[PDB]
Length: 219
Image (cartoon, rainbow, N blue to C red; front, side, top):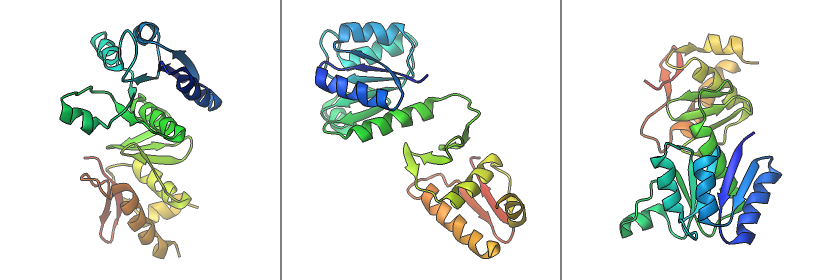
């Protein structure tokens, strides 16, 4: 099962995070100082580690650095006071995988944990990737930039097919044959997909070959 380590010395907050994650069926170990935190982070396998920037004995950055120095590459979510940019402008560059400045919603913390898991998961049967786009084919959800893409069900079916066949042009005819009028709406679906997947991103995944078909590209 997916394992999380929480290292946080404010015990009510530590326990809030821990129990909130347990309610979602994560397996969680909680540490209330950097001594036990460091020991767990270096010596026991986890899928994600959540550290406070401030901890007794060894602070969150110290734990993160020791992990990396020891070959433990598990993603780390650092709970902080300030944003990464705010720390960087001060001269502190921690190199954590993600940062969650206070105050935050537990919902946001859980989302950030889930994004770290999906982005770092190895070769999956139920994970498809096209560039930096991730499809969780087990739940029929799509993500990019650590954010869920709000696709309609039809949009997802089309996207999955294109991604399954990435870098190959797929015709309307091939799509029609594989998906559950059609001709008219397909262009709208693709236009909407293009907006939802590629807006704000330099690398454009959704492509159209005029009069032929569509293709999800990552080369």
